[PDB]
Amino acid sequence: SDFPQHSQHVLEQLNQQRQLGLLCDCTFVVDGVHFKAHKAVLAACSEYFKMLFVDKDVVHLDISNAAGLGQVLEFMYTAKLSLSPENVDDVLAVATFLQMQDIITACHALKSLAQTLQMEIPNFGNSILECLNEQRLQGLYCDVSVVVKGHAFKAHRAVLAASSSYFRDLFNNSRSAVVELPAAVQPQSFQQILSFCYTGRLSDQDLLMYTAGFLQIQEIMEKGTEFFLK
Image (cartoon, rainbow, N blue to C red):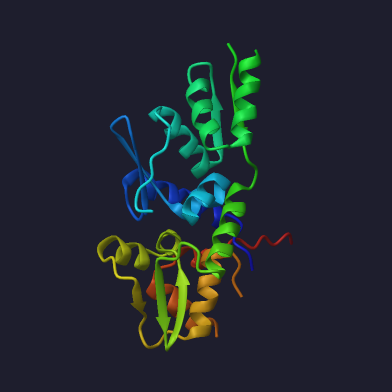
């Protein structure tokens, strides 16, 4: 069975982690403002960032508008952009540096013209989650392994924390890169859980629930609604 809001909930959590500083792994400082973010989301949104990361502790970028950076980030984390003649140049200079062709063409359009322009990339959640899964299957940006009876599972701290309060609480307090789970947890069970965290699809039903409870993955308990029409 599928959990059709799962992706969205993950993106909203990843976004909230950002706005509070929690569980991020990189930071932009510009004009005194700090913006924390996750490499894996940046790279899933932008070929520029992906390429930048194949190369360094620190890198200098030729962006100087903070509000602009702030909105490109917001877009990457919510799939919404609202362009006005108040902000269009800001955004444009940032999108131009990052070679984000979408945002650029949209800025050019608005500018060719009171003029407002909203964009929304449909099913963004889904797309981003798919990229995070793919990254995960190759060890890209994974900053933790979860060991279950000798089997290591690579993953992203931030994604696990998006679905599990156990992992949210653990990673907010410790920075250890290896994590063992209680002996009751089986590899097949954690597997299914891991797949659900990364895909929104779930397929012993008791041990799975036990494991979900220990991880405090509340969304798995949402069974939906049966509507009997007679």
